[PDB]
Image: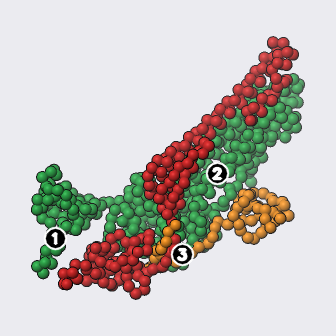
Chain colours: A red, B green, C orange
Amino acid sequence: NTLVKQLSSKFGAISSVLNDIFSRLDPPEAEVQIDRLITGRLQSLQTYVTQQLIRAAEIRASANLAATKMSECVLGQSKRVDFCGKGYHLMSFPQSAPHGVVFLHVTYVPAQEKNFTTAPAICHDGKAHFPREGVFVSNGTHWFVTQRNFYEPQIITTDNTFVSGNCDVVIGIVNNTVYDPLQPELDS
Amino acid sequence: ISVTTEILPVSMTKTSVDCTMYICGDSTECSNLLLQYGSFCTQLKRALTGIAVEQDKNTQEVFAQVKQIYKTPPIKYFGGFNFSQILPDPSKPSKRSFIEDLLFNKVTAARDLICAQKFKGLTVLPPLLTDEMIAQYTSALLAGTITSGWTFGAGAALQIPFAMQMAYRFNGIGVTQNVLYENQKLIANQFNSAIGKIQDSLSSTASALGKLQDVVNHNAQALNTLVKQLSSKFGAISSVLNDIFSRLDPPEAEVQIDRLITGRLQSLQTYVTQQLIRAAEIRASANLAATKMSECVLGQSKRVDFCGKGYHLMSFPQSAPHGVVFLHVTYVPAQEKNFTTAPAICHDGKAHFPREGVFVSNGTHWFVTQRNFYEPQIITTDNTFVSGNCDVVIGIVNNTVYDPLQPELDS
Amino acid sequence: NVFQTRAGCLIGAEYVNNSYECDIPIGAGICASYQTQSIIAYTMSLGAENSVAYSNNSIAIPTNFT
């Protein structure tokens, strides 16, 4: 619209149209006015082209980002934080829109938290025990092992713990019992 | 344990230009003559306003990522780690930290240049967010990462002791937790020494903030050349237009005025185009900084050479004039030793492959060890699995495997 | 009325001591909005204020998902 509206400028000439300039002045003198008009219009069109180029570069950057998002979020599962949504990414769906794409992100969010008391290791039979893929918790009386992102208490055993060293070097260790699931069937 | 510093520019300086004062000065005749060229200044105002709002959008996107403002509890024990230099200092009125103060002091009758440029139609607008608000965002992020961990980037903040968080990160990089639980004091001392070295380097070295200084210098040079362009004839008798009007008749004064107007308009166009290109580059840098903040501060990244040189552990943000600074805490091995290995163990006519580690030998015996730390253990059936006979694998060796059940059968 | 901000002088808006999310950005941490039947200029609120209970031996574990 502004490129169209620039056509009414005079640029210092005697008129904004060409036919009256050519129908009122001799060839020796109309040249200056014609040159002024031509130079002004050329400058306007060049400025338009430059702005279009810059905007095209920005659109290209956005398109590259969208292509990367389609490659990772949709065709696979992403471990990147805050890339395919807020939370823990599960999956995604694409939809089309005029000059654009819309991504629907299905994600997982925890809720209904609860407090607990924990210790890093358990000292038993003069040895320190560490969890394999969980965390030690206590409800005030007993001790359990639970997964990090969901509450699922379990009994401490040898199958879900591993031993390394004595229990006089780790800060915060506590005393408890580790249940051996081989002897009770052997003694029965 | 290594700490590394990274500097990223975020935003630019917002500028506004007055056409009439810059071009025609205080002369009314030029003001009347200027109207003939049409709409050449509304476009300039639109472009400059777009850049100005873009800068605020950049800052808001980079820094405003937490819904709630957290505070550290009064007790300052975090398993031996100090953190007293990066946390807010209530004594100073700016509510900033030591490193932040050093960074701000690092980058910097008679009439000031700012007033002289203002008196020619070039003005600077203030940003939406003051420095105090950016400091508060940084403090909230630091408190959230110290107290909660990475849980506050995907939901509610759940408290966890610092040692257990470090154990989880060690498990993430590929080392078991017992290493941390047995070398807590050494790791804490290394971290404190690294922070002290960063302090010393910041206090002594004064060339670590090149990028922001380059941005400031580029803006200053652009303004300087724009101002200097006002004293060129462009082919007329003189730069000053009142002398042109007084000396000679209107018929040629019109030509001289047209020459000056065209030259000044061309200079303004060039300035606007260069500003647009620079703003695009700054926006790209801001997008990179926002991605880095979301990926290295609110979580742990497995990408190589992204959140530091080495094995990534964690990171901390700090503010800087028109930019952000990242402190990356990473893990690097040292004191390596040679060993002899084999791909599998042939025992009882069966091939045995390790479950997590690698097989090593110290000259006479054979052990299984984790990949990134030397911790030998006896080869048993608990850390090994069997697949096929031992006449196919190339390089298999002979040894014995211990079964933890037969000893109990006889005892 | 008259108010003096680091971005200049504001006429026609009344300053209040509360804090809301920004609607029209003026600058230097000052925003404006149309509320109450009047125009009010205020200071931005970054967000809600929170504190987390931290100790040697306390953890928080979720029990449900969304």
Q: Where is residue B83 in the image (x, y as percent from the top left)?
A: 48, 70
- Residue most toward the top? A27
Residue at numbered disc 3: C52
Residue visible at 54% across and 54% down in the picture: A104
Mark number, residue B110: none
Dot in front, 2 or 1: 1
The answer to whether marks 2 and 1 mark residues whose Cβ atoms lie closer than 8 Å is no
Q: Is residue B344 left or right of residue B5?
A: left
Q: Is mark 1 on a helix, strand or loop?
A: loop
Of the residues shown, which amino acid type is indicated by label 2? Answer: Gln
Q: Which chain carries label 1?
A: B
Residue designated by label 1: B403
Residue A18 in sight from this viewpoint: yes
Which type of secondary structure does the marked residue at label 2 adopt? helix
* Label whose residue precedes the other's in the sequence (2 or 1): 2
How packed is label 3: few (under 14 Cα within 10 Å), some, or many (20 or more)?
A: some
Viewer-proximal residue among A39 and A182: A182
Query: How many marks can you see?
Result: 3
> What residue does disc 2 label?
B55
The span from disc 2 to disc 1 (Cα, nearest Å) is 67 Å
x, y (%) of residue A60?
56, 40
Using residue A179 as the reference point, say whether residue B250 is left or right of it. Answer: right
Residue at the (81%, 63%) spot, across then down = C39
Residue at 62% across, 57% down: B60
Residue type of the residue flagged with mark 3: Val
Question: Marks 1 and 3, how far apart in space?
Answer: 49 Å
The N terminus of chain C lies in which quarter of the figure?
bottom right
Mark 3 element type: loop
Same chain for marks 2 and 1? yes
Q: Which amino acid does label 1 sit on?
A: Asp
| Residue A35 image position (x, y, % from top left) | 76, 21
